[PDB]
Image 1: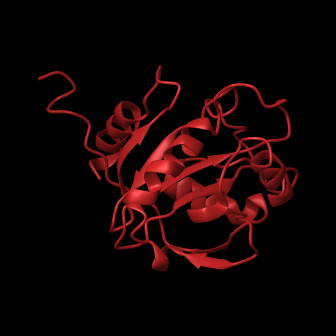
Image 2: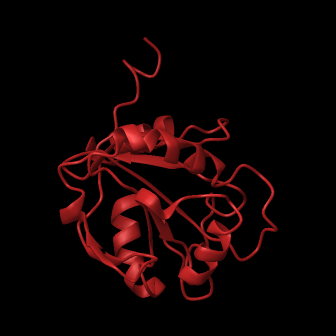
Length: 174
């Protein structure tokens, strides 16, 4: 045994309704039941170079097999300055497929705040990100209830299973 008997997570992402990069409305309603993948990023600074979305892009392939109605959601970090147009432009660089990939607006950080706080601690307002600034591109695997059950970090080094698990227990063992 090491980190106990592994790093089970249960990170409940509070349901809400969002608009995707198609201007199309989607809620957790459409995903709760399913094992849907999640991430969140900006693209505003950066030239495009590291394997940032590359992991997601690679997994988009696998997704065909997982498809059922699992979607890989990807919400905007600081959507006021970035905006879904930047995610679109970035998707025009990282050679990805909207195919079965819901890039979500979230809208103003006031809107994004409570959502991303509860869900992931991932707001931009008072904190800048004190972690999710430099080059993080962490996966979440969001379970059927809406609780996350695995993470990964793509570029390895800080897999985020371990951290989110530890935070899970430390919080109040969700």
